[PDB]
Image 1 (cartoon, rainbow, N blue to C red):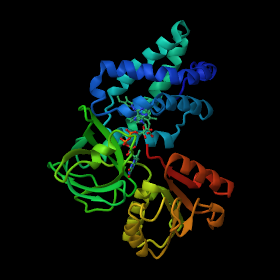
Image 2: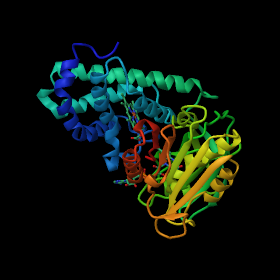
Image 3: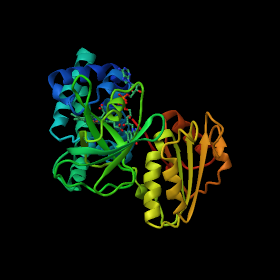
Length: 383
Ligand SMILES: Cc1cc2nc3c(=O)[nH]c(=O)nc-3n(C[C@H](O)[C@H](O)[C@H](O)COP(=O)(O)OP(=O)(O)OC[C@H]3O[C@@H](n4cnc5c(N)ncnc54)[C@H](O)[C@@H]3O)c2cc1C
Ligand code: HEM
């Protein structure tokens, strides 16, 4: 059952008002919920995302995007958004009963904001929208959990190897420290790793899995000088115990391969190399015949994380080319910004982007201007 005929005109008429009030409703929703359920800050919600504010708007904002979608495309869902959210939720171990929690505090905040304007017709219609989306996500998350090799949401790992590989990137290898079986990861997937803040709150962050033994989880963490957890993760000593989630994510090598022989173009900046290296290592293990073009940006070659390993893996591919651009020093294959018009990208190529939001926005724009189909551009936001 999709969006009811009764609710459609109400959602249609109130969508602008609701979208306008979302930034105001969000902090009240979270403030109320996290006062009643402080346990949810100790292992689930990111304190930094609450303090930044804009980030935390995504939950309610996706509800507005969803409402607009089901009005334009009835009995269908924005599957890309649902899949991304479900994989994140599964990484964080979200259980279906908590959708009742979010409903309670979200709609309480709607009531507080709108006051007497929150009449039954409006609350009824938006409640229907909420539960359509919640049910879809719950169903996706249930299927994700069924794929795992274990029945937990995170398990204890020991840090067995730690290497400072650039001025601000630490390459970390973990192995299980309890007897929980590991789910095999797919190239491009990430894990959530957990540590406590200085004042004792458990907090997760996501990192892309890197080539390792099947008995290991390997990640490369770039220091965010204005973030809370990367300093904590990078200061763990060998032997430290941290919890790691099961692996998830829908931005995998299979997602980029639309047909058996389509070429791949992988474009990254900074620590956005991490899915690229995962993809290249897998393609090399598969003895892929695809044409693979890798364009990586860094401030300098010395600051390019994992460049040596990426180049070694790329040498194993039949038809791979790697080009590094340097944006501060002049030692790259090229200097300055990637100019995609110079690239010969055919209409059957898939293009993958991973870098800072601004970098990806400019690349996506210039790709579209150069005639690359939006449907062929795939991206991975780190945050
Ligand atoms: C799928 C996925 C894969 C990822 N893979 C990698 C990877 O391989 N390597 C990697 O290095 N990272 C990766 N990331 C990013 C990573 O998950 C973290 O976002 C990143 O490491 C920053 O974490 P942090 O705790 O240091 O920053 P956070 O504490 O989360 O802060 C992030 C930003 O929030 C703002 N902020 C923080 N505190 C406040 C405050 N008090 N007030 C206002 N604003 C504030 C700042 O602008 C800050 O830069 C990935 C993310 C995702 C979603
Ligand atoms: C219909 C209900 C919900 C919707 C539409 C929704 C939507 C979203 C979206 C869009 C994101 C960002 C995904 C991304 O980063 O790409 C997100 C992240 C997140 N969600 Fe959900 N969500 C819902 C329910 C819940 C519930 C019930 C919980 C827990 C009680 C929860 C906890 C989280 C957490 C912890 C994050 C990580 C970001 C953060 O720490 O703030 N969500 N959600």
